[PDB]
Image (tube, coloured by chain):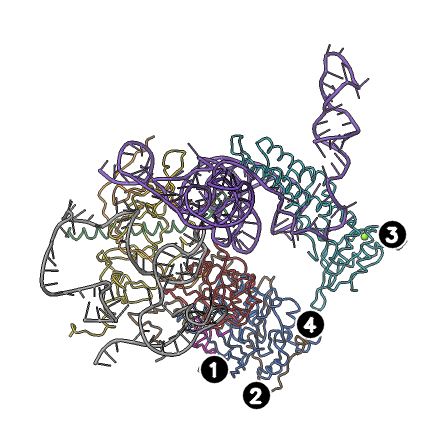
Chain colours: A yellow, B blue, C brown, D red, E orange, F green, G cyan, I purple
RNA sequence: GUGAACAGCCUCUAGUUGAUAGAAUAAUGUAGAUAAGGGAAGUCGGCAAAAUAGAUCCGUAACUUCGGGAUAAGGAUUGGC
RNA sequence: GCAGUCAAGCGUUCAUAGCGACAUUGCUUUUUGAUUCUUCGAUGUCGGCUCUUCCUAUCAUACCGAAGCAGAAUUCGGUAAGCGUUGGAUUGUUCACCCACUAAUAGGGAACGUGAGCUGGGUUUAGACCGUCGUGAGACAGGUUAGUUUUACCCUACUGAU
């Protein structure tokens, strides 16, 4: 009776005041957070063509996926690839501080070497890296000839 | 006749492969297990840190002799490329596709005669005889199904697990053309193929393997230079007790 | 008879004309015995590992221990991919 | 991890909770296994201790030999059928759940294992890797 | 009574109050200290986040069980155009 | 096991900062300060074009 | 178990064995009640102090009786070292005095909980608790002379050497100051004193060596004198059953 | 019309378009749903929900007052031209 | 607790009046780990789901001390409540005991926490059957079935928002 998505017992008879720590209902999200120890993999350059090409792939392509990022344009600028998940959403502004102290663990010392960068389209099930792949694999169409 | 322990496991044939002209070792952690092979083998044969399908158990996935090396299907292209870079041209290295992946449990062999699982297909049985340059026989040790886990071979002699009947030993030695003893390794483990590795001039086994058990292994593979294996009658006094 | 299972060795019955002998490469017979306490002995890359870091920290180059016709390309990188259809399917002799 | 398990066990998805009937893969003489508890589990209010691929769980035989039945004994999971994650880029899942029965040392009981054993289990238990006819 | 069954608290009391922040650009609360022999070095930089993508990598991690093996994982890509200086502010230390 | 703020580990971690892991940062703060000096020289060359 | 005896935890003197149990029930069980409380809360308060303390002496005494080797039906030799060294009469009396004391604590606990349910106030329930802990204290004060003995036998039975009578041994016997300590020093890795006087060793020292891929254990005697062949020291009597029972060279 | 049918669903003759409305889609609700792996471990208790269902053919136990039990259980099949 | 052996202390000036601590010695169903499956009757109503806090009399982790402690494994004690303390079976039951994991499954308070938060399982009306008692109406808190769960929009507290 009266709900199931809630807290059942919210207090006791003494003290006769709802405590500051009993999980009430309210705002979720749009807070400011600090998440530390994120590791930069790649510092690309906007004037540099073939950003997405590693030492392995040898395919001239930029990290901008097919039809671009979803809800965002194209990376034709300098970019920082960092692992994990920065708090915040797309088309928002982040601020990148540097480390606040000398980091001790061996994980903060390793030199990475990226072997393949994905650039398939994020607006659906991306199955091709470049549009040259898709027109190669599909064959030709009615609207081409 | 060397005792060696992978990280804290007495199992060696799981974690290493040893033939007459090469050796294969896992990559886990640190180079203590790799050093013990350089203590015995020296620089005379290549010893290879390798992984098979991104694993550490490389002695039960592969199978081979001094002529050839067989890897299963799940061996990636980089790891197949890595084996040929280290090993010389005298070895043949070929990826084999089957139903069953683990070739170590299924193929036990010396440089000359191989034994296979019964359910193996004849389109691989042709390939085994062609790559490894050996004969192939379809047989089971004591009605146990995996001939690679429960038997260990070299050109010198052969060792089987103690459930083998005496009638089964006399039949099976005509196929392998080597002497056969029922034995245990690492204090009574039935799995005698996984416990140890052996070639014609070296045997490497676990630390748990007791001194009566080294006496059997040093005998049947004739590890000292003046051993005709007939000293097992002199070593029968250890055998009656143990 | 169960201890006799661990005593009775088997005999081959010799079942061919074809002779089968063990193979030892002559560098093994030429090889000296390793000695634990000695001013001069080979390094045994445990000790290569020891002088630059301990056990878990030491980075083994898996390369620089294999055979090629030229040492100068021992550290090169396999491309492993072009646009489609990865490179390991195409390369061959001739 | 615990005793007998060589190396560390990475994170894979929790597929088998308490009270899960799974097939008995080996030739020991049992048909199916009933999970009652998972060794190396956590402690949290109202959670069920969930097994995964390659864990030693206590399992009673429901159908099989009467010698094996009515006594609790350890068992190692070899097939999962819940989608888990390999660290190379694929998610895979087997067809059914399966387990082989063992001593607390981590040694096998039977001689053979039918069907494919998981790759995550085959690195973890060497005695399972000795009896594994088919890996992956 | 005495709760009969212990359980950890729900929520983290460090992040109180949960409320909407003052602006869509969060201010930085603290900076790296000062290494006063080094050359002049800007402590931070600000850019625009844009999506996510996957990266495979040959993991060069000694000691792990994934040493010398390939690892797929997810990264973020933050669009980071160059940033131009327009002002200088100095701060005097007070006992306030 | 020992907690994060124990006196034993924080004495142990302070020695590693005296050793290897500060050398990599002091190598890092020299390479980045080199490129920031070449940030002015590229942007002064474009100012020379308008002087023409 | 066989072949060694080290897994016996401890045994405390009776003044301290009482102080362990009673201070434990002051710390574990609650202590704060009022006369204004409802009387079933008062009764179940004092029932638990008799019950938990009653279990408290038993769990101590259950650990003693299981841990001692049960000198009857072990082995004819391992019974017989303890016969000469530990005096089987005084061994079996004191371990029986604990088992009698274990039943009486269960007796007082199962009787006074039955009486404490008929209490009618705080005061009558307070008297039945103090009489219950007092009568449990009386049994333990009576148990002083066993527990003082059993601590001093717990030490040397931990320091007995491991011999297996079924495995292959060989005895070394003779007079005092012959050289049978010096023989044992060079034949194996063992710390046996080689001092030139009569009775250097006072226990059966054991050394282990190998011949033809086997384990041989070599056992030394303190050296013996026949003088009556009837009555003898506790030291020299250790040899004879080490001669009689062990089937070897 | 579909169908065993005055079932349910849609339509013809006839009748009504009345029941305060407009804009947005937070929490919690009332009403109605779907869910990976495990299948009652939930709980006073399988409460609830899921499962089965129409039809032709094969097949049906203990027991029984010989009438029943019985649609027992269980198993094959269904469109179009 | 009683029956004793004492005497460190006391009795207005004092041994032997009169007590009399720590001690000490004895039984209340078996000095030889054999037994001994003895769970010998609580007469006012709480239990659990959810969810916070607090006490330390500390089960686990931290650093220590002593041992009649080789190592390992334990036993006893100190500072210490920062952090954790579970999954199931029978019962309306708390309690109780078993199976199993685990580093450990520590003890208690907050109207014996907690009903405009729930549940209605139990307790506490009317219906009804059985057993005993009563000539009879009926009694029994002996046993067993079936039984209406109402309100927040107000002030304040608290989570959010101008
Ligand atoms: Mg002497």
Residue B106 at x, y percent in the picture: 51, 76
**On the rendered image, what quadrant is the C terminus of chain D found in?**
bottom left
The residue lying toward the viewer, choosing from D113 and B206, is D113
Instruction: Estimate how packed mark 1 is, as few (under 14), some (14 to 19) or many (20 or more) residues with alpha carbons within 10 Å.
Output: some
Q: What mark, if any, has residue B125 been given in the picture?
A: 1
Q: Do the residues labelled 4 and 2 touch (CB within 8 Å)?
A: no
Front: mark 3 or 4: 3
Q: How far apart are marks 3 and 4 (CA)?
A: 45 Å
Instruction: Estimate how packed mark 4 is, as few (under 14), some (14 to 19) or many (20 or more) residues with alpha carbons within 10 Å.
Output: many
Residue I140 at x, y percent in the picture: 51, 41
**Residue behind label 3 places its C-beta within 8 angstroms of ligand 1:** no
**Residue behind label 1 places its C-beta within 8 angstroms of ligand 1:** no
* SS type, badge 2: loop
State the count of labels.
4
Q: Disc 1: which chain?
A: B
Residue C6 visible in this rendered orientation of the protein: yes
The residue lying toward the viewer, choosing from A48 and E57, is E57
Q: How far apart are marks 1 and 3 (CA)?
A: 81 Å
**Residue E74's image quarter?**
bottom left
- The residue that mark 2 highlights is C18
- The answer as to whether the residues below labels 1 and 4 share one chain is yes
Which residue is the extreme one toward the right? G228
Q: Disc 2: which chain?
A: C
Q: Do the residues labelled 2 and 1 touch (CB within 8 Å)?
A: no
* SS type, badge 1: helix
Instruction: Estimate how packed mark 2 is, as few (under 14), some (14 to 19) or many (20 or more) residues with alpha carbons within 10 Å.
Output: few
- The residue that mark 4 highlights is B239
């Amino acid at each position: 009776h009266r709900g199931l998505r809630k807290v059942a017992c919210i207090g006791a008879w003494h003290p006769a005041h709802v405590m500051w720590s009993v999980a009430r209902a309210g705002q979720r999200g749009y807070h400011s957070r600090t998440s530390i120890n994120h590791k930069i993999y790649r510092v690309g350059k906007g004037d540099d063509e073939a950003n997405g090409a590693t030492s392995f792939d040898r395919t001239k392509k930029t990290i901008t996926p097919m039809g671009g990022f979803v809800h965002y344009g194209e990376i034709k600028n300098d970019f920082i690839m960092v692992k994990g998940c920065i708090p915040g959403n797309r088309k928002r502004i982040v601020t990148l501080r540097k480390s606040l102290y000398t980091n001790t663990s061996r994980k903060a010392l390793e030199e990475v070497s990226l072997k393949w960068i994905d650039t398939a389209s994020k607006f659906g099930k991306g199955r091709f890296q470049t549009p040259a792949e898709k027109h190669a694999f599909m064959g030709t169409l009615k609207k081409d000839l | 006749a060397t005792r060696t322990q992978f990280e804290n496991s007495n199992e060696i044939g799981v974690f290493s492969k040893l033939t007459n002209t090469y050796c294969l070792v896992a990559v886990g952690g640190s180079e203590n297990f790799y050093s013990a092979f350089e203590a015995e083998l020296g620089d005379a044969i290549p010893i290879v840190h390798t992984t098979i399908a991104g694993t550490r158990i490389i002695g039960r996935m592969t199978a081979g002799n001094r002529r050839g090396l067989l890897v299963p299907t799940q061996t990636t292209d980089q790891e197949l490329q890595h084996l040929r870079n280290s090993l010389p041209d005298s070895v043949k290295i070929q990826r084999v596709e089957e139903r069953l992946s683990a070739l170590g449990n299924v193929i036990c062999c010396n440089d000359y005669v191989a034994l296979v699982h019964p359910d193996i297909d004849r389109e691989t049985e042709e390939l085994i005889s062609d790559v490894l340059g050996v004969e192939v026989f379809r047989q089971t040790i004591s009605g146990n199904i995996l001939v690679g886990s429960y038997c260990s071979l070299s050109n010198q002699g052969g060792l089987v697990h103690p459930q083998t009947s005496v009638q089964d030993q006399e039949e099976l030695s005509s196929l392998l053309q080597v002497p056969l003893v029922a034995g245990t390794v690492n204090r009574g483990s039935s799995v005698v193929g996984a416990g140890m590795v052996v070639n014609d001039y070296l045997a490497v086994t676990g630390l748990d393997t007791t001194a009566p058990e080294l006496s059997v292994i040093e005998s049947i593979f004739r590890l000292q230079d003046a051993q005709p294996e007939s000293i097992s009658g002199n070593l029968r006094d250890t055998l009656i007790e143990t | 008879n169960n201890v006799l299972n661990k005593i009775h060795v088997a005999q081959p019955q010799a079942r061919d004309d074809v002779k089968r002998t063990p193979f030892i490469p002559e560098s093994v017979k030429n090889l000296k015995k390793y000695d634990p306490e000695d001013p001069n002995r080979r390094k045994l890359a445990r000790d290569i590992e020891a002088e630059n870091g301990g056990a878990g920290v030491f980075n083994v180059n898996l390369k620089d221990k294999y055979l090629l016709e030229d040492d100068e390309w021992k550290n090169d990188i396999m491309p492993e991919i072009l646009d489609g259809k990865n490179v390991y399917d195409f390369l061959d002799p001739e | 991890s615990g005793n007998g398990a060589q190396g560390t066990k990475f994170r894979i998805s929790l597929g088998l909770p308490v009270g899960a009937i799974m097939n008995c893969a080996d030739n020991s003489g049992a048909r199916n296994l009933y999970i009652i508890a998972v060794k190396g589990s956590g402690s949290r209010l109202n959670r069920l201790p969930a097994a995964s691929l390659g864990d030693m769980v206590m399992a009673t035989v429901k159908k099989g030999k009467p010698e094996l039945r009515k006594k609790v004994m350890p068992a190692i999971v070899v097939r999962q059928a819940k989608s888990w994650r390999r660290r190379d880029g694929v998610f895979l899942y087997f067809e059914d759940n399966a387990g082989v029965i063992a001593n607390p040392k981590g040694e096998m009981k039977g001689s053979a294992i039918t069907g494919p054993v998981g790759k995550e289990c085959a690195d973890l238990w060497p005695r399972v890797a000795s009896n594994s006819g088919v890996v992956v | 009574s005495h709760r009969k069954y212990e359980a950890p608290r729900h929520g983290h009391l460090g992040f109180l109050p949960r409320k909407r922040a003052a602006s869509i650009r969060a201010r930085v609360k603290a900076f790296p200290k000062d290494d006063r022999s080094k050359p002049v070095a800007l402590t931070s930089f600000l850019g625009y986040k844009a999506g996510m993508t996957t990266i495979v990598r040959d993991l060069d991690r000694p000691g792990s069980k994934f040493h010398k093996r390939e690892v797929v994982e997810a990264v973020t890509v933050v669009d980071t155009p160059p940033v131009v200086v327009v002002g200088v502010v100095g701060y005097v230390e007070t006992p306030r | 096991a020992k907690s994060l703020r124990a006196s034993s580990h924080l004495n142990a971690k302070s020695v590693k900062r005296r050793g290897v892991f500060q050398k990599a940062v002091d190598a890092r703060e020299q390479r980045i300060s080199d490129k920031l000096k070449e940030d002015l020289l590229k942007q002064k060359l474009e100012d020379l074009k308008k002087k023409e | 178990m066989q072949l060694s005896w080290k897994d016996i935890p401890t045994v405390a003197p009776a003044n301290d064995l009482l102080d362990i149990v009673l201070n434990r029930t002051q710390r574990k069980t609650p202590t704060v009640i009022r006369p204004g409380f409802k009387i079933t809360r008062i009764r179940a308060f004092y029932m638990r102090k008799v019950k938990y303390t009653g279990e408290g002496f038993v769990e101590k005494f259950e650990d003693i009786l299981k841990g001692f080797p049960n000198i009857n039906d072990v082995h004819p030799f391992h019974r017989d070292l303890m016969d000469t060294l530990y005096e089987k009469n005084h061994y079996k009396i004191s371990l029986a005095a604990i088992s009698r004391a274990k039943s009486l604590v269960e007796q007082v606990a199962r009787d006074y909980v039955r009486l404490l349910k008929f209490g009618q106030s705080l005061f009558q329930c307070k008297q039945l608790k103090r009489a219950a802990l007092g009568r449990m204290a009386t049994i333990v004060k009576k148990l002083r002379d066993p527990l003082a003995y059993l601590e001093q036998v717990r030490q040397h039975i931990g320091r007995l050497p491991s011999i297996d009578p079924n495995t292959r041994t060989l005895l070394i016997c003779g007079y005092p100051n012959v050289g049978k300590s010096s023989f044992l020093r060079c034949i194996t890795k063992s710390d046996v004193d080689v001092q030139p006087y009569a009775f250097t060793t006072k226990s059966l020292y054991v050394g282990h060596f190998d011949y033809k891929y086997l384990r041989f254990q070599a056992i030394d005697t303190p050296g013996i004198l026949d003088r009556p062949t009837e009555e003898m020291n506790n030291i020299e009597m250790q040899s004879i059953y080490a001669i009689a029972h062990l089937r070897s060279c």
